[PDB]
Image (cartoon, rainbow, N blue to C red):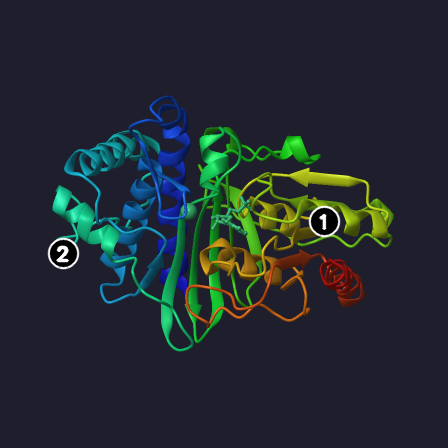
Amino acid sequence: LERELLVATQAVRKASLLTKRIQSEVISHKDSTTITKNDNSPVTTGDYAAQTIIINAIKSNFPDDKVVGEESSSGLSDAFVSGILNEIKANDEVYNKNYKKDDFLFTNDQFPLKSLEDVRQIIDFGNYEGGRKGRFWCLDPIDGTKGFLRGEQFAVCLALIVDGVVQLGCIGCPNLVLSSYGAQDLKGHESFGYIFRAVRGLGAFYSPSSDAESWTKIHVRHLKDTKDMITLEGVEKGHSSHDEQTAIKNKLNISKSLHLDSQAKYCLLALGLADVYLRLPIKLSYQEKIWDHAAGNVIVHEAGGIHTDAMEDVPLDFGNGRTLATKGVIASSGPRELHDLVVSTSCDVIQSR
Ligand SMILES: Nc1ncnc2c1ncn2[C@@H]1O[C@H](COP(=O)(O)O)[C@@H](O)[C@H]1O
Ligand code: NA
């Protein structure tokens, strides 16, 4: 999967810079850069620009490839689309001065990414429904859009699924400063953060996004007692059952928690800076989206961790379409005894409502 990893990495890299660069402007013009979707969730110029860069890179390199992307261009006005295009081109002017990759194409004759109709066409390639067989890309162009809009953590996530199993993942964390989580930062991290990646069977690695050439292997840690561990949880109260997560902590004597938006959580897990990622469901009717977890799935696995749902303690199934059929998500450092204690506690807490 050599070409695929290169494409994915460069695609995320470029989109990581664009999204980092525009975060403030988006926030400041949060009347004209942001749209509300049918569930009231937000989507910005940044989300679409990221999606455009990424899909255009995939399609330039792999013309027939299928993509499951959360966004679609229907309804986007020309003015809105012109703003997406302008951000891509401004980003290119900065990006090409320092980060061009030799012998790598983001655009070609078939997909030149020059017009508003090109933009629309590329966005609209994200409409695959996934499923059990064959190869397809899974993208969350801005992962944790509320984190983005709060000026806090967000990520840019891409994965390749083949026959329902995630084979490759790439997560850009443009605002992730390791010194905030008790770790050292690497040279070059300050321009646009870090990129994390893994291929099934080949290990998990990271690099500053500005580098993306020299890769450092990462692995979860293994603390022996739960009273020393650290949880990872989201910030948004509506995205997970915080009170039930607290019950879990209290039962396990955990007194250290980190809250942040996006799959950057899986990256901190995989680096060994925390131990248990909790994502219990508030409502059992919710079906988790694959693009919120697929990149992280393979990164955690290759880092030596475990990833299941939050009730049954079964592995997540990335072949069910756009959603996970199970309820909630729990990831940890493992071993299995730690993981199972956590998930069984979650199960019991939920059942006791
Ligand atoms: N009710 C919900 N339960 C779980 N996840 C949700 C819910 N509503 C939205 N989300 C997802 O939360 C993701 C961001 O996760 P996070 O930053 O970890 O809180 C988004 O990309 C949404 O798809
Ligand atoms: Na998103």
Does any portion of residue 2 appear in the rendered image? Answer: yes
- Mark 1 secondary-structure assignment: helix
Looking at the image, residue 49 lies above or below residue 289: above
Q: Give the answer, above or below, for where 190 lies relative to 232.
A: above
x and y percent of residue 56 in the render?
25, 51
Residue 110, label in figure = 2
In x, y percent, where is residue 325? 53, 68
Of 212 and 51, nearer the camera is 51
Q: Residue, x 61% and y 63% (percent of image)? A: 301
Residue 77 in the image, given as x and y percentages of width and height = 18, 39
The amino acid type, in three-letter code, at marker 2 is Gln
Q: Nearer the viewer, residue 206 or 169?
A: 169
Give the quarter of the image for residue 350: bottom right
The amino acid type, in three-letter code, at marker 1 is Gln
Residue that badge 1 annotates: 245
> Is residue 174 visible in the rendered structure shown here?
no
User: Residue at left 30%, top 43%?
Assistant: 48
Q: Residues within 10 Å of mark 2 (few under 14, many from 20)?
A: few
Q: What element does badge 2 sit on?
A: loop
> Is residue 36 shown left or right of residue 325?
left
